[PDB]
Image (cartoon, rainbow over all chains, first blue to last red; front, side, top):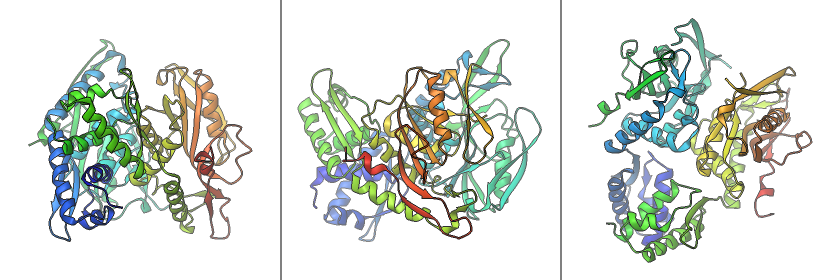
Length: 269
Length: 270
């Protein structure tokens, strides 16, 4: 059933938005709308231009009758900065101060609207990494991992803090003892390029634990993103990582809490 | 300024990313610096397309207090096709688990699958007045978020570990009493809660969750599970929707039975 341009633009927009990071043959669309490849290409130029102008993302086109298009979610620096500032202000509330130097995030992480933004910012920053899968550890980071994975078009793998399983010992920020994390061996292909995502990085042991867990799968760290990094941790982590926010050494007794920008802007050109 | 074409693309993106939200025509008129008449015409193009393509319903509410609202909906034919495909995939003997369980980890890890399940849940409960989605850690978490994002509501996660509320219940794995808790600061009392879970075997977990909401003057708006163990619709007095039915996996024999759940009852049988 043929759609005229207006109907195709609408359906193509929905289809692209719901199939990010997937190379779609022009052929799939020409047959879907029983339209000429040339009309589709024309429609895609309109979408590509609107997507860039509105800060939705990039449409990459591969020419030829055998060509295709790929939608790449991307966030403009201006929106990233504004979103992060707003989010930081929201967290810089003494009522969130938690024992041990932690921050209460449960409410913000319960909101798909916020997670969507966070996920897209991670997806944007790591758009060009060849990611095969997103990994995080139960449980606070799970929703962040799915948000990022949905923009990236890859599966999520959840490491458990408890079949043929692989296990690694690691230490946590509570400046505590040795714990173990595991992941079933049939949960991930060898050589996978992994984006590690977590909500909070205090000491860096949880992430180092996941990075070490990856060596057991002969997998590679494709990138590392965290919502909040405790002040001065660039030290305890060997791999590059991206953070949206920095929690400056909080104090429960003084009931003060400072929150600054993470290092994310370094990732914008 | 936006030419009609660009405006349709942006409007489409805008509606798709703001479901279950009443948006005043004025907002669009201002965004595109255009007459309301032109916006309404675009909305008709989108409504028609969304309807024919099975994306959802664009609801236009007349009046200055009105506006437009995008409601994600899934056609019955697509839901049946999707559930069957999902069922066939789970009926693989390789997913065998002791105790009458099936391996769901790999599918619960795919946003593509989650998106569909979340949409089907959001579609069935589209007209219920839901304020929050609730699930219990940790398997159901991604399904909960998927449903919640289509419904425009926050997610609340019950912990099985300050002013905390608690309930005790018996899982389907162990007969030992368990405790699920939820911070009092995690949910507004009187909320219409859509409960979501991956697998309902005994029914205790969901029952426990139903009791826990009592403690908040909360009202169960609906219950949705991905898989229900054969023989559970006599262990729950509450109405629930399930996508698949898992017939007691063949312990000794390497076979597994999967059939549609009761979801068709929630489509146009209403």
